[PDB]
Image (tube, rainbow, N blue to C red; front, top):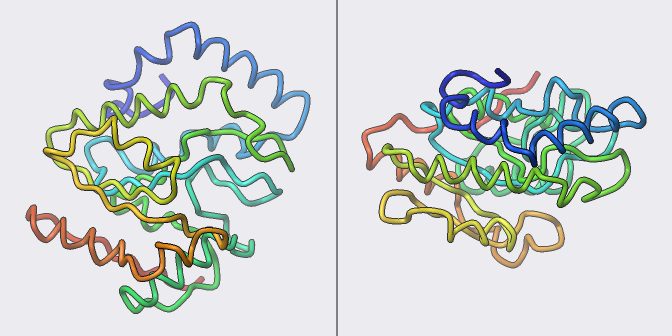
Length: 223
């Protein structure tokens, strides 16, 4: 059993499939033979922090950060002591305009995860220094499944879909129940084209205000 019961009751069948066994053998080799991020114990951290029952918001990312000391097994987040990726910085600038929060002196989003924000990357491992190096090795099939089981959940989920790849997931989601907040990506590449001004945090809390749920405290506090 790799995950807590709330997730494992939904996903155990995926872990038994040939594609996962192949992925698991491939990762055993790569963790032994070269530098893979995040640390192997951290691969599923998004799901460890936020249980299936606790999920309120899903923020989809691509693959893990590929530099030393960055990834934590969470989309967008970095560990403490590390500088903020430009996508994260930009996220904090929009948060500041939207909610008012000051920018933190670290880029760890663990507080969001603890409040029900699922920080899911669609690919869960990467070789150091090599973007998208574990693309197409099986992760995308598993994370599509994670989206499927969230779509099937009775209680409504708010999906934040930044950029074109995340928006492709809309087809998997049942929009008669769930809420979609989508924009261009926060990356300095795509940010000024639809992320800034979109007010994604204010808009999620509103979707929570509406379902009788507690809002997220989207502000992080300094170390």
